[PDB]
Image: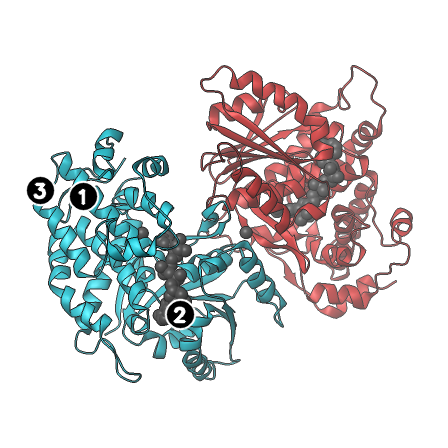
Chain colours: A red, B cyan
Amino acid sequence: NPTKISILGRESIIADFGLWRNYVAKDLISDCSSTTYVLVTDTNIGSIYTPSFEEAFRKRAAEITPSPRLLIYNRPPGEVSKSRQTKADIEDWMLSQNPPCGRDTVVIALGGGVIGDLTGFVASTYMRGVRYVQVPTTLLAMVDSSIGGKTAIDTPLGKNLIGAIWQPTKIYIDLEFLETLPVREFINGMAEVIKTAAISSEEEFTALEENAETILKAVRREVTPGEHRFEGTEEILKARILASARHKAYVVSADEREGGLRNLLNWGHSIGHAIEAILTPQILHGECVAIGMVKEAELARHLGILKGVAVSRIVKCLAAYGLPTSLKDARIRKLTAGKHCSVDQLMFNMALKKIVLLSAIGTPYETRASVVANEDIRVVLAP
Amino acid sequence: NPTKISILGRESIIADFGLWRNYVAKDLISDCSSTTYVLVTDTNIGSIYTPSFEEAFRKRAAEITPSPRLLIYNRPPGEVSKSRQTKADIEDWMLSQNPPCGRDTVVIALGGGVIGDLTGFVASTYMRGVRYVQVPTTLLAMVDSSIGGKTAIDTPLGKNLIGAIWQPTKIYIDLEFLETLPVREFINGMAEVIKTAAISSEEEFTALEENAETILKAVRREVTPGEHRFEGTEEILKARILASARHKAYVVSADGGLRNLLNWGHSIGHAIEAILTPQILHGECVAIGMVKEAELARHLGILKGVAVSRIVKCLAAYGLPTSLKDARIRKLTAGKHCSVDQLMFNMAKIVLLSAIGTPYETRASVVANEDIRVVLAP
Ligand SMILES: NC(=O)c1ccc[n+]([C@@H]2O[C@H](COP(=O)([O-])OP(=O)(O)OC[C@H]3O[C@@H](n4cnc5c(N)ncnc54)[C@H](O)[C@@H]3O)[C@@H](O)[C@H]2O)c1
Ligand SMILES: NC(=O)c1ccc[n+]([C@@H]2O[C@H](COP(=O)([O-])OP(=O)(O)OC[C@H]3O[C@@H](n4cnc5c(N)ncnc54)[C@H](O)[C@@H]3O)[C@@H](O)[C@H]2O)c1
Ligand SMILES: [Cl-]
Ligand SMILES: [Zn+2]
Ligand SMILES: [Zn+2]
């Protein structure tokens, strides 16, 4: 059965195994009536998933007169496509169609965080705004990037500098996409899942601790023909992933005077972003956020706010899912030959302190990021 | 007297003679607190108006501490600057400042429709959105472009293709800008003023008819550097221009319907413009469109022939063309012809008038292509 989660007081999220394979096309043409559908993705994702959809779309466009059209745009993979150049590329491409794409256009964002931010931003300004849907194909996109409307592209000077808040009409979460997602990317996305649980539900966190071995085994297993990577553990994977997605939706949907409940989502990102500013692009975002979570967890313990046992759980849980819990992680070192993260550099990258503090697994200290002394931060980052 | 109007619920429009010279700076720093203010304009407008403001800003920044900063960006004049390149150059420039312009930045759009659309769009996406104010310097901008939140840039394949709805925090209308606005541009802007009146108030339309000689004289007379072009007729100019502006503001606030009325004379007007541009200006084309669309309604037995004539006399009174055969226009468009086919083709529903200050339907009406032709053809 398809699970539904709402965003900003309305239906928006539809999650299940096989949506892309048999549900999205029909749904779009039905609930997102348009004459034109523009699908944006990269060559990796697309070469694997675009063919089936083209057929499923053709099969759904036929039971209608006249038949809506599906236009496909394949961008090269990587953070590099999240640029002004590609935004203008996709746009001119869309304007140059016969007939050109109009304000009724429904853009389909089939990809991870990169394609998501790019496509969302394209849609936000196309003729001052057109509808679009998110079809996250990475774990991180499913529970984070595709939720909340934050759209943008990069500039040589920094990440997500030019963009917009543009909400998607719908977010289709097809867990089957995780069947072909590279093991490292999957692990990477788990950083947000564990973060979410860590700051919202102790029960959820425990479920993550208990489901690690099973989940990871499935993520690494050799799939025999006729099988689906996650057969046998579908409910576990769905309950775990949707718990995070759902939380993100709740936080983003909760306003009517809140102050900064959204702030708690940055737990582990204060230090995590600092670390990433140095180790990127060798080390992924989640990998850096994982380490940031451990450091920030130690900090709170250092300030006598977090019990030492919670730190250890936080550490075993991340490692159980394959995430690094230290800056000298064997894997990290091999990928970043000649990169060091000195306290000074980290204390610097951070100043460019307010760290969400935890008082217990599933329980934040303040309802917002707390203010901590630079000296206390340095001690934590000491060798 | 600093007049105030409301857009989208409440006040945002401030109109008067001299606002730029001694009010915006203080106002911005007070009502739009920020550490950074980015002024965007073109070399024409800026070379005339940026110096005073710089001083007026410095004079107001000193009163507050630490003193804010004013960053100026001068773009070349023309429709050509309303492009992706200029948007990116402005963005890159802002981000390059030391320190980089943050989300607290308040962008000042000092210019006409071009600078307005460009700057508004820049502001809408800068770090996903930052505040900005409109300081329209052309008549058309004062009563139309600077109002409504419509922002964008052009593409070789068309105008305003990439943009967004981004409302300005404030719209400062300093009528003194019209002192240096080229006569042709001023006349051009009058097309929207006359259009607005034509579809909203018969009294207002009549006031435009009676002010015609006076306004034009002020516009066409030779003013000497130091004397104000509009001394003696300031209330007339203010009441006329603000009337148009306040109406656009009203409709933009109501809301597919009431907004459709704002397009009277633009159905044919845009078709004509698609051919005659860039030689012929938007207002000049909209003027002719108004006459055509007015005769169409007369053709359909909805408009009295007398209203058509008044519409025709008023446009002409203000120096706007009322036919494709206009000498100015023919001379200016040598090498071009608006065949009826091309116009119909370009047209691919017109707002009909039942009387001066009175629309037919509450929205654009559906008319048969044949009735249109018998009105486009000679
Ligand atoms: N609020 C927001 O909008 C927000 C917040 C967090 C992250 N992000 C953005 O997300 C981006 C990173 O996104 P990401 O971690 O999803 O990485 P990504 O989109 O770069 O995807 C990683 C890799 O996986 C491949 N891939 C994607 N789906 C696949 C699948 N199911 N099968 C096979 N290959 C697949 C891609 O081709 C790519 O190589 C960053 O640029 C970041 O700024 C945005
Ligand atoms: N909804 C909207 O936002 C909207 C609606 C209608 C028109 N527009 C757009 O507006 C643009 C047209 O703008 P416009 O007609 O105001 O012309 P414009 O901005 O191109 O200005 C015309 C000329 O006058 C000069 N100038 C401007 N003000 C001056 C002043 N006070 N003193 C001296 N010289 C001055 C300029 O340098 C320029 O050369 C078009 O690009 C059009 O697409 C936007
Ligand atoms: Cl853009
Ligand atoms: Zn993150
Ligand atoms: Zn107009």
Position of A218 relative to B51 (above/below)? above
Q: CA distance from mark 2 to mark 3?
A: 49 Å
Asked if residue A5 can be seen in this view, the reply is yes
Work out whether disc 2 and disc 1 sit on a shared chain: yes
Dot 1 falls on a residue whose secondary structure is helix
Q: Residues within 10 Å of mark 2 (few under 14, many from 20)?
A: few
> Could you say where residue B131 lies in the image, as x and y percent from the top left?
46, 61
- In terms of sequence position, does the residue under pointer 2 or pointer 3 come before the other? 2
Query: Residue at horizontal 36%, vertical 75%?
Result: B20
**Which chain is home to disc 2?**
B
Which quarter of the image is occupied by the N terminus of chain B?
bottom left
Q: Nearer the viewer, mark 2 or mark 3?
A: 3
Work out whether disc 3 and disc 1 sit on a shared chain: yes
> Could you say where residue A312 lies in the image, as x and y percent from the top left?
81, 48
Query: Residue at horizontal 45%, vertical 80%?
Result: B54
Q: CA distance from mark 2 to mark 1?
A: 44 Å
Q: Quadrant of residue A107?
A: top right
Q: CA distance from mark 3 to mark 1?
A: 10 Å
Dot 3 falls on a residue whose secondary structure is loop
> Could you say where residue B274 lies in the image, as x and y percent from the top left?
37, 45
Q: Which mark is residue B294?
A: 1
Q: Nearer the viewer, residue B259 or A309?
A: B259
| B316 sits left or right of B44 in the view | left
- In terms of sequence position, does the residue under pointer 2 or pointer 1 come before the other? 2
Which residue, given by chain and number where applicable, does mark 2 sit on? B31
Q: Quadrant of residue A209?
A: top right
